[PDB]
Each structure stands twice: as C-alpha cells, then as structure tokens.
Length: 346
Image 1: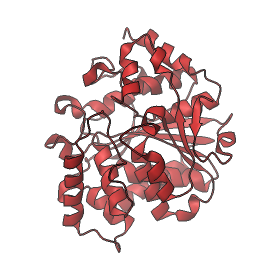
Image 2: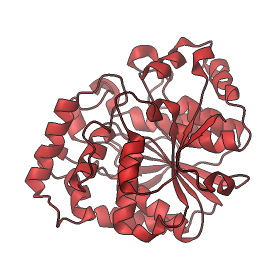
Image 3: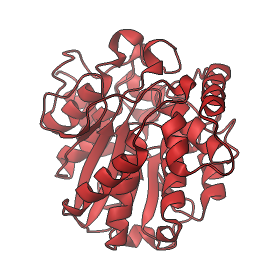
C-alpha cells in the first residue's frame, strides 16, 4: 500500500495493534575525525547523534541549537522519527554506545568510549560484552514490539566491513547517507583493517566486530535477540547498516531468524537506491522480511524533503522503521510530511 514488502511472511499482521518501544542506539567512530568516510561535516560530526535523539525525545536538539538540516539543506531524518513519535504516542528511550558528545536528555549509557580506529582493525575490545549488555538490557524493557534504530556517522563503512568480513558480497551494495559515496576510500579503510586484525574464514563474529564493527551493532544484536527469544517482533529500523546487523544476529543465533520475528524496516529511498542493493545483501543472509515506508515527499511544501527523492539523505534514527510501524498502524503517510512542514518554525 504505502509500504513496500519483500518477504512479508505474515509479519505485518504481527506488528499490527501491538504496543511499541522505540530506541535509537548512537555511536561515534574515531576514524571519522581524521578520514572523510562519512557525509556528516567534521565540524559537527561529534554532535550529530545526540542532537538527533534529543529531537526525538525532547522535541529539539540541545547541544546543537540549529534546526534539523544538513549540507544540502535536507531535514535530517530525526524529523521523521519525531513526527511518528508524536503522532503515534510512541514511548522512546535512547542508548549511547560511544557518542563523542553525550545527550542532554536522559539516555541509557552502555559504553561511554567511542568505537575506535577502523583502518587499524581496532574498532573495539568487547563486542561480546556489548552484545550481552544489550541482551540483558532488553530483558528489562517491556513492550509488545521493539523498533530499534541507529545513528552512527560512518556507520556505512563499518556496515561494509562487517559484511565483507563475514564473507558476504557487499561491495557495490552498502551505500551512503548522501548521493556521493566515497567508495574507493571506504573499502580501502575496511580492507586495511581486516588485514591488520587478521580476519579470515575461521574468524568469529566477535572478532570481525572487534576489527571493523561499530559498537551500535552488538548492542542492537543483543536487543533484538532478546525480544525475539521472548516471541516479540523486532523492527531493525535502518537501511543497509541493519543488514550488517542482521548478519551478526545470524552468526550469534541463526535459529532466531527461523522465527519470523525480526524484520528490517527502512525507507523507500534506501530500498530504491540506485547505488545500492539492500534486497541483495539480505537475500544472502536469509529469508527475512524487508519493509520500506513511502513518504510522498514529491508533494512536500518544504523543498528539503524532495531531496530525499534524489538520494541526498535517505534514512537514519529509525525513521524508515518507525514509519513502517506507524503506517501499518493507520497513520496516513502525508500526516508525516505535514507534521514536519508545521514544525519547521523551531
């Protein structure tokens, strides 16, 4: 309808009428401060993830005082997530797995240290701990459904690395936030780091993460496995990075994906990315529902939204996913667009 479904195997009936909790897991990547692997400008990259979740939780950013707009002038996808949170009354609580600058709203601290130098094969020490920290947290979170999103700048390069390190064919398939994608750079950083950590076929998932992952990933894997083991549906609210994460879920608990309980929820912009292949990556991982939200941003009064139609900003902060949740639960898609148009004064 206003949802694009790839292997909807009675999953949409599973998220209908259920009570959600939304959470966004934020992290920073040390590489990102010296190497322009991400589209977020260096001058503001440290502050970006907190500012995102502040907008979702509180209604405005508090470290950054400026409005939801990126280079290109596009409203950042937190505007979508917020819209949904306000129009569908979705309780939300956000998690820090290493943001350079911490949020000024209440947040769950899980790891205060950033993800490390990806090109040096030292992303982290404790992918297993982070996984467990996320698992145990999930037990104490009560909801009939989890929508778990992310906000990690440079996360598109760690998604590439982790998938490549688990032996998937991902090369032209993981993409970028922007239209421009410095692929040559990104893949050199990732391969450089797999080389240095000594990653191979015999490597464990915790090694690959430790080499080139980002800390958001284990936590979300823990969170998701936890809800899935309790027979609760989970929407991995992100694009191509969530495929990486799905890949990790498969390594830790292959038999959880046999339950039809974990879906990727993203936007039409990611799905229909000319420069990437979410569907393709996910076919290699397993038969998992992939669902994208339609925004009808072509009709938007605010021109920054139409930039989504071009690829200039595609997804983030669980926007794709929380909108899937909303739309299936009877939010008219245009209500999202209008919300954002009305809200643009703060």
